[PDB]
Image (spheres, coloured by chain):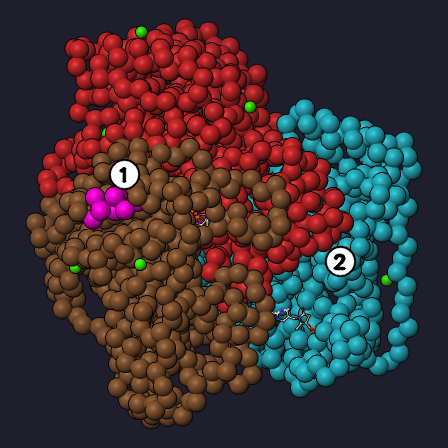
Chain colours: A brown, B red, C cyan
């Protein structure tokens, strides 16, 4: 067998059937003879390739396979890899390298020092020392991406390796099963359970690894047993809990003092599947107030090590959430009361307040919609206004890197064909990965793109105003016609200049058979 | 003085007056109070920021200054940095980092292990250990980028450093002059000159560092004295010689055997300002035929070390070319005969042959036009059909990384306002950095963009055919409306479906006052 | 030809005939069939291997070739590489790697991520992608080590590569000549010369790259023409000037304020072949006083970039010193007056003051002796008391890394068999690389080792006293019998408890036919 045939067999046997890519010559011997049972998804720029793959992996809860071209292709994707690192996305990034005989002279298209290029944004990065090693290296990549804490990996393969003979002993790779589905030993788990049962006013904080693990329902049971309020950890990449459940208390503000104030009076705070904490703004103060103890369950040693406070347990989130939910006592305390309905913001017949948009989306979208957010000045309002009952309903760039939501929304929609995906993207953010729209058109992936057009990098203008910072250049983005960009890439385009037009356009978009972009004129 | 004021003073004193950027919050304390004598050039994605800066630096023959946001912004630019490495572009890449007090907890927007992120594509990469070090680190960056061999550098600066007090002793940085304008010692230079004078059939090969050094005219004198044919080294990023000079012999094919055959019978081959050699295709054979000696002059130790053949001298190209041109004897041999006019390809009233496009551009463009090439299946024909008399007339992605020409053409046009820039870009390549078009519109930088629309990744289809490779996915890019994309970003848009429409559109574009995109229907 | 035969041919053709090594199995296919015209120098630990090679390279002014075993051998040498980086030592470090078929499984003796292991202490680090690339990679290593600024490089080679067929086209590597012997262009050199001629009170500062280049005599001529005092730059790794020449002013103190005070009143300070500056102690103040301009000539871009003051020129030190010495005018100013004789310190019939030792060495040693210094509390006195007339007469650990002098003294003595080497090493420092003594015994390399036994890490005790730092552990090293250690490794051993015994032992050592260690009881 050739290295090509053995490698595709390994991929198939390990559950991979899709290649997200942008082709080049170094990968031609990999891509030729492409197997009929595999699908290739082309995108026009590598940030888009990796963003699509990332959304696919996060929504599918399985690894996604990528093929890029050499250093330039890899490099074009490194912003996307920053997000994938922070979201623990299981991405297998392969990159085509020059033929081994041309690497020393540094021929055009040579990826110099290839394994160092994606660092520090990958869990493992490698170039094999021989062709016959390629299947084994691919096995390593698959498992490294997939073991907790999941994350992106990188494998560079010389052009000429694919046609070489494989080692027959590579067959032992095909059906390897590698598990990291582990939980705290019984003795120490019983201590934790007793601490939770004994708490007088517990609180729960959930992060994105809960949604990745599909541990959401277990966390609902846990919260109901403990009669505890539930927050989402700051800078949330995913939504880990039903947002109209009575226990839900919303997105934590991403500041040190704000969080310790929120947690004051709670004697035990159990954090599951989040870093402690993904703060953002400068908000100095106490990490915790006196009388609060924090206990973190995390799938990631790097998270446990860097927490500035609390105990930690490094384990699989799915396994731990299920165990905890089924072991804790039912508290006799009263169940928390649901948060009230958010206020309706006054809206005239002009430009749309973002709150209006979110309220209308919540009114018209299916109950099993999936939302993506890259509307950076409106996140707090979005989190208050969308009733997200189901797992897998929200994605936000986990490293804050813009250019995620537009391509990721296409990958999510590919992963969840029955669930309508609605990406809410600012006019600034929409540009970073604009060319991803073409993939939605070409493959007829029916994502809806809602462009929040305020003409500015609003979150930056806001921050400069808080700072009283004057004479800051580059904060405005006038003169972009998003309907024309959509037309450029073959996607149906609508405008919404007022509330009536927003409802009419959303009605049209929801019944369409293909992707749709709606440009919304929002208040500036 | 603050670190901000000292740093901007250093930049001004060192000749920097322009910041190419995409803003974020980590850089707000750098960008606020932006000096009135500086200009900020915004682009909508960081590949575009760096590509624009790169074209500006290459055409201006001086460093260009960039400011990006953290890891995601840096990462979005890494493909662009691959090209800048290969072109020896002097780019000073700064990236905003989180406040020092938030780096340990890895707050959102922290650039983890920042100095490692752009490696191996930078000459120097650094994060200062204290605020007061920032001016000194900036000095280091400026000089590292600017010393031969020029190249990109990276500096990560925490948000909170800018407002801190600077060290008064930083004033010693302001007027430092650092020179690498060096040439071979007299004794060894006399040996080289004697070897050139004694050659019976010398040949010259020129690469991009000749054009960077503006050594073109000196090389013309050298060629005329030695009565030697002149080739451009393969995979050419720049044009180092007038292409209708009698000695000019064109672009070398990027293959080992092809080049040694071309050089057969030439007893001494002098290579200036090129790697030896930037081969591309697999074309095995002899590096040199018997009877050929090669001597390379390079500004880059890494080039000299990796050449598989020949002697080398590591020195400044400008200094060496000027010395050699003025020291060699006038040979009594006959001056080479100019290459004939290229053939006119038969053209019907339908889709355009690329040869037709290039011939029409050469007919209608000013004699001091500047061309950029990212039409990857048509490069050989382009090089034969454009009369480029002047230095600085050609750019091509030096690492083969697509997404260079569209933004670089804007930066070149900013650098050379009197010289009409014409970027010839394939329909595939145009997508990688499409959003750069907006910068041309916003700043009214009057670049002309010629999109070669054949509906395919033609160079890849070509290569797959040579290989007889079947079932290769992802090679076609149907369904892109480039006039609509231009409209999207505010750039005047024309179509050319046939030769009459090509001439009419070029006539319109050449008289326009702003940027123009022309979508040309080319033969598939 | 095999890769082994081609590689040894390349080495021989490039002037390498000695391998400094500690063997292991991964290198057995390299070391077998060892050519009869090569010499292998074994040392018992890899810090010793590299230190010996380093002294050999520095004294020979040519590259030295090393072979180590995998990661553990490489790692044992990394302290030695820190010194070699700072001294610009041209070292070619090869390390044996596992067979390619065993690298993926990470068999015992695999060097994981090998090229990253020695970073950041090497100029270039590489593992070839195929066996046939090994000769080309070796060529790259040779030239990278040897081009200015010289320095160490690293090449990792899989076991199985050596026996494979080489590429016949590797013959083009054998006789490549690569030059970096360059100087400032004539126009800018004339400006520099005019600035030197016009100075009213010039000063010269020389660093180790002057001695490496054998530019010492040229610098003497330069100093005499300009009638300028000459200092050695701080933390001096080498001696660049005759220390009893009338212009010589000694070792600069390694502090910011001390140096600017020393240079006050000097209108032009010309620094050659040194960083600006290798400060050590905290001594804050002005980099330069008003009225002093500094101009640096350096072979190293990294030095030129980081200087906090002055202009710089990046060029070959040999070429620049020769040009400057022969172009400057003869000043009519008076020649500086020689420094007086140092004072004789009162010495009783007990333990030796270090000043006594140095005075006695200067009295009894040949005029062409070579000294090494790793007696860290006595350096200033050593520099005042030794008349070093000739180039190549002094070495000191260039990164301050102890464990250099003992092995380096053996390599220097191998390089300079007619020049008596005398290493003056503290009792603390002697331990780091003690096993190097065996190589001197086995190869009968007749180095004299003078152990300054004060029972303490004296320079650290001194510093703790300046700090008024109390309760510092680990500063005393009682209970080491150096005569017994010498016996252990086969080296003749003497003691000197008083001045009479010091003279008698030195008389014995100087007439011996093999290496000798003298343990001197020095004042504490
Ligand atoms: C790749 C990248 N570049 C720049 C930024 C900086 N950035 C920028 C540019 C923001 C403005 C986004 O504007 P928008 O129009 O998408 O949304 P708002 O107007 O609601 O802020 S928010 C922010 O962090 C970033 N996070 N990621
Ligand atoms: C960033 C990146 N991704 C992918 C490639 C691979 N690539 C691709 C995708 C090519 C096709 C470019 O198509 P085009 O339409 O711009 O021009 P032609 O149709 O004339 O080839 S040529 C080539 O090397 C690349 N070099 N750089
Ligand atoms: C490898 C290493 N480890 C530790 C040190 C720290 N060090 C130490 C341990 C010194 C004391 C050396 O003692 P000595 O006996 O050799 O000489 P003195 O008694 O004259 O100081 S000086 C100094 O910088 C070092 N420089 N290098
Ligand atoms: Ca409602
Ligand atoms: Ca699915
Ligand atoms: Ca906006
Ligand atoms: Ca014509
Ligand atoms: Ca200009
Ligand atoms: Ca095309
Ligand atoms: Ca004396
Ligand atoms: Ca010798
Ligand atoms: Ca001591
Ligand atoms: Mg990197
Ligand atoms: Mg290392």
Instruction: Tell me whether the residue at label 1 lies in contact with that at label 2, contact meaning CB atoms closer than 8 angstroms.
Output: no
Q: Main secondary structure of the magenta part?
A: helix
- Residue under the point 80% across and 51% down: C286
Give the residue at mark 1.
A494
- A488 falls in the magenta region: no
Residue placed most toward the observer, A346 or A55: A346
Q: Residues within 10 Å of mark 1 (few under 14, many from 20)?
A: many
Subunit that carries the residue with mark 1: A
Q: Residue furthest left?
A: A36
According to the picture, the residue beneath numbered tag 2 turns out to be C254
Answer whether residue C90 is visible to the viewer in this image. Answer: no
- Distance of label 1 from label 2 (alpha carbons): 71 Å
In this rendering, the answer to whether B154 lies above or below B469 is below
- C215 over A78 or under it: above or below: above
Tell me the SS state at disc 1: strand
Front of the two marks 1 and 2: 1
**Residue sitting at x 57%, y 65%:** A283
Judge from the rendering whether residue A350 lies leftward or rightward of residue B115; answer left or right.
Answer: left
Check the residue under mark 2 and report the chain it is in: C
Instruction: Tell me where residue C115 appears, x and y as whole percent.
Output: 41, 57
Q: Which residues are magenta?
A: A502-510
Q: Quadrant of residue B437?
A: top left
Q: Position of residue B175 (x, y in %)?
A: 71, 37
């Amino acid at each position: 067998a050739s290295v090509h045939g053995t490698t595709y067999e390994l991929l198939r046997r390990q559950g991979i059937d899709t290649v997200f890519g942008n082709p080049g010559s170094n990968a031609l011997p990999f891509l030729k003879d492409f197997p009929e049972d595999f699908r290739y998804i082309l995108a026009l720029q590598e940030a888009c390739v990796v963003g699509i793959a990332d959304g696919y992996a996060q929504a599918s809860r399985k690894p996604a396979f990528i093929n890029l071209h050499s250093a330039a292709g890899t490099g074009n994707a490194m912003g996307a890899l920053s997000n994938a690192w922070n979201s623990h996305s299981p991405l297998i990034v392969t990159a085509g390298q020059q033929t081994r005989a041309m690497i020393g002279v540094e021929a055009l298209l040579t990826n110099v020092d290839a394994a160092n290029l994606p660092r520090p944004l990958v869990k493992w990065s490698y170039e094999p020392a021989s062709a016959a090693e390629v299947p084994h290296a691919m096995s390593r990549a698959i498992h490294m991406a997939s073991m907790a804490p999941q994350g992106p990996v990188y494998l560079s393969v010389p052009y000429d390796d694919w046609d070489k003979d494989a080692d027959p002993q590579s067959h032992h790779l095909f059906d390897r099963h590698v598990s990291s589905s582990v939980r705290l030993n019984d003795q120490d788990l019983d201590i934790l359970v007793k601490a939770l049962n004994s708490a007088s006013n517990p609180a729960i904080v959930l992060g994105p690894d809960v949604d990745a693990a599909n541990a959401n329902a277990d966390c609902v049971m846990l919260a109901e047993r403990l009669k505890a309020p539930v927050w989402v950890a700051p800078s949330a990449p995913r939504c880990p809990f039903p947002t109209r459940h009575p226990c839900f208390r919303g997105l934590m503000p991403a500041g040190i003092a704000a969080i310790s104030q929120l947690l004051e009076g709670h004697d035990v705070v159990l954090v599951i599947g989040a870093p402690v904490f993904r703060y953002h703004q400068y908000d100095p103060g106490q990490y915790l107030k006196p009388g609060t103890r924090l206990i973190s369950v995390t799938c990631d040693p790097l998270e446990a090590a860097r927490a500035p406070m609390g105990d930690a347990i490094v384990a699989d989130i799915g396994a731990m959430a299920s165990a905890l939910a089924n072991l804790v006592e039912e508290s006799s305390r009263q169940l928390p009361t649901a948060a009230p309905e958010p206020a309706k913001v006054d809206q005239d017949a002009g430009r749309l307040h973002p709150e209006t948009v979110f309220d209308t989306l919540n009114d018209m979208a299916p109950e099993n919609a999936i939302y993506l957010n890259e509307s950076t000045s409106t996140t707090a309002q979005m989190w208050q206004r969308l009733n997200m009952r189901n797992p897998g309903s929200y994605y936000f760039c986990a490293a804050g890197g813009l250019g995620f939501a537009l391509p990721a929304a296409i990958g999510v929609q590919l992963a969840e064909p029955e669930r309508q995906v609605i990406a809410v993207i600012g006019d600034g953010s929409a540009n970073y990965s604009i060319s991803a729209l073409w993939t939605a058109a070409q493959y007829n992936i029916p994502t809806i793109f809602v462009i929040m057009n305020n003409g500015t990098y609003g979150a930056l203008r806001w921050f400069a105003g808080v700072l009283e910072a004057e004479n800051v250049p580059g904060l405005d983005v006038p003169g972009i016609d998003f309907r024309a960009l959509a037309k450029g890439y073959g996607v149906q385009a609508l405008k919404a200049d007022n509330l009536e037009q927003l409802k009419g356009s959303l009605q049209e978009a929801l019944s369409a058979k293909g992707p749709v972009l709606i440009e919304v004129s929002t208040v500036s």
